[PDB]
Image: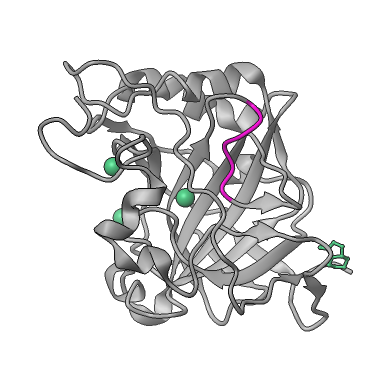
């Protein structure tokens, strides 16, 4: 049971975000994520470029319940699924995506917009090819680019359904399954308008390597889709059930950072 045999970071009362600094001191660092996006402080930057999403040749491989979310993993041994343009210099390869979500529809996102919490947030994680591999990229201030997409509850997202339907097979921590031919273009909204700022990954080890690109337009998913997320488990098989919900970190201090908008 959580925190009895040993301690591990998580999202509970004894090991949640407010505790993470005890094992990962960078949790109190100068470029932590997520942040609140104050729409009356972020300035339009006309030097930013349109975001170039080239996911046509993506190769998904597996889906994994890692005890704090599920990752959909991709073959990143070539430039098969890349993010370019905008604030980015060069080419960033997609390695995985995952979500953060709530126990109820009024919370779940990590970023907020004028303090608004969405029901969930999708993170597509990419690494800068100039550093050769993800592990070297996460030793650099421009090593990663994360495309963040808000989810609200409304109409269903057809391109999400294949994800929803596989979750029964990865209910518990450590379970993985084959998950080929998944097209992440089915998770995008219509507009690629975005905000951008320098930050970190939002789970330990909280690495301060990320250029965040947060889309303004949410995607809609149905109540039934997000309910299926909430049937996942943080625990392993044969351990008592602890539902995988509220796996989000709250907003962190902006400090001296600037949030830029791609749109006037
Ligand atoms: O994010 C927002 O929202 C309002 C303002 C418009 N100009 C771009 C930056 N802003
Ligand atoms: Hg974990
Ligand atoms: Hg890989
Ligand atoms: Zn994330």
Left-right relation of 192 to 175 = right
The structure residue drawn at horizontal position 43% and vertical position 18%, both measured from the top left corner, is: 231
Percent across and percent down for residue 168 are 37, 18
The structure residue drawn at horizontal position 37% and vertical position 43%, both measured from the top left corner, is: 16
Residue stretch in magenta: 105-110
Percent across and percent down for residue 55 are 56, 55
Q: Is residue 227 above or below residue 194?
A: above
* Residue 18 can be seen, yes or no: yes
Looking at the image, the residue that sits furthest to the right is 264
Percent across and percent down for residue 195 are 71, 64
Q: Nearer the viewer, residue 80 or 110?
A: 110
Residue 159 belongs to the span the image colors magenta: no
The picture quadrant where one finds residue 154 is top right
Q: Main secondary structure of the magenta part?
A: loop
Q: Nearer the viewer, residue 100 or 73?
A: 100
Percent across and percent down for residue 259 are 69, 71
The structure residue drawn at horizontal position 41% and vertical position 42%, both measured from the top left corner, is: 72
- The image quadrant where one finds the N terminus is top left
The structure residue drawn at horizontal position 25% and vertical position 30%, both measured from the top left corner, is: 173
* Residue 78 can be seen, yes or no: no
Q: Nearer the viewer, residue 133 or 256?
A: 256
Looking at the image, the residue that sits furthest to the left is 5
The picture quadrant where one finds residue 143 is bottom left
Q: Is residue 17 above or below residue 230?
A: below
- The image quadrant where one finds the C terminus is bottom right
Q: How many marks?
A: 0
Left-right relation of 213 to 137 = right
Identify the image's colour scheme: rainbow, by chain, secondary structure or one colour: one colour
């Amino acid at each position: 049971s959580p925190e009895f045999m040993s301690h591990h970071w998580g999202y509970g009362k004894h090991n949640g975000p407010e505790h993470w600094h005890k094992d990962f001191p960078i949790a109190k660092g100068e470029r932590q994520s997520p942040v609140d996006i104050d729409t009356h402080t972020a300035k339009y930057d006309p030097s930013l470029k349109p975001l170039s999403v080239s996911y046509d040749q993506a190769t998904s491989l597996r889906i994994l319940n890692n005890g704090h979310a599920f990752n959909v993993e991709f073959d990143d041994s070539q430039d098969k699924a890349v993010l370019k343009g905008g604030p980015l210099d060069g080419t960033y390869r997609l390695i995985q995506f995952h979500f953060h979500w709530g126990s109820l529809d009024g919370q779940g996102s990590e970023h907020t917009v004028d303090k608004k919490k969405y029901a969930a947030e999708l993170h597509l994680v990419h690494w800068n090819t100039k550093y050769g591999d993800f592990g070297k990229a996460v030793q650099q201030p421009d090593g990663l680019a994360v495309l963040g997409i808000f989810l609200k509850v409304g109409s269903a997202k057809p391109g999400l359904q294949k994800v929803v339907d596989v979750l029964d097979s990865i209910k518990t921590k450590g379970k993985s399954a084959d998950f080929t031919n998944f097209d992440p273009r089915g998770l995008l909204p219509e507009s690629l308008d975005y905000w951008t700022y320098p930050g970190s990954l939002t789970t330990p080890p909280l690495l301060e390597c990320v250029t965040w690109i947060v889309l303004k337009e949410p995607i809609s998913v149905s109540s039934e889709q997000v309910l299926k997320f909430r049937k996942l488990n943080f625990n392993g098989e044969g351990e008592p059930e602890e539902l995988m919900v509220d796996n989000w970190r709250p907003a962190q201090p902006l400090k001296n950072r600037q949030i830029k908008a791609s749109f006037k």
